[PDB]
Amino acid sequence: GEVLFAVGGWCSGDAISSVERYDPQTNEWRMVASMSKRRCGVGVSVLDDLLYAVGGHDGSSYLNSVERYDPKTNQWSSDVAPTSTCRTSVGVAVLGGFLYAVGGQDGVSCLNIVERYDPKENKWTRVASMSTRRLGVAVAVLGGFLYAVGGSDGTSPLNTVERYNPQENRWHTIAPMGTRRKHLGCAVYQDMIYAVGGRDDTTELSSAERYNPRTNQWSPVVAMTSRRSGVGLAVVNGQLMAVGGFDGTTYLKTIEVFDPDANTWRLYGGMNYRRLGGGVGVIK
Image (cartoon, rainbow, N blue to C red):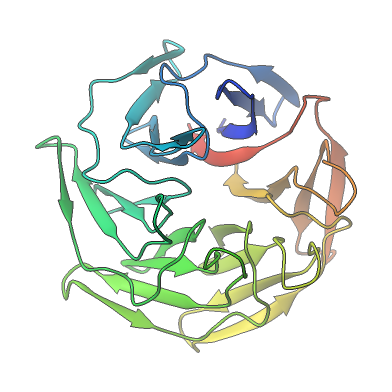
């Protein structure tokens, strides 16, 4: 059974991020060990069955911090090289055994920076930058490409979608989403990229859409029950699930699971934590 981990759905005033664990087989949430470094706004992904947390900020200070969490020991380690730049709201994903850290924000601006981590060498390297500067980009990997979807330019949500080919070391701008989305969830499901929730220019979104690389098209997907900006999206035991988020009024303590046969999202209660969700990674 796969387990979902979620980092940073809540961040305390004193910069402690929540670290939550969800086992969908038993339907149990737990709090697990906090990161060693005080920080919020981390980006997370899973590499070799460890949860990596990259970047962030501690109040006004932006970080180059990297930590990795072992679910077998319930311990975070600070044994990894830091990134070369300090930045928050970075998008993280793994392609071809490297961990990529995409975009974000520092004191000065939103960023188009892309760095790659080689676990064999324990070294970060700048690779090709995105064509667009953006923070909080949602990342997904499909077909040998790394996708950078949506995000924000500092104020406004984006519909931009770019993908990176590591053999060419180049980003290419592809079909934009139908809606501008910051604070969105993105996950690969059934060989398509799903983008769910977020916030457009006017409102938090319940809407969803999916990208098919074969056709280079985004198509609308049936809406969730709730609007969810800040939503965590992941595939867990083969099921697409959206976690938490802000509906315009309040922070939600529910999840939704996509049921493609019924063509509906099924709503389930979660745990009454201060915030449910954050940056997500799935471990078996």
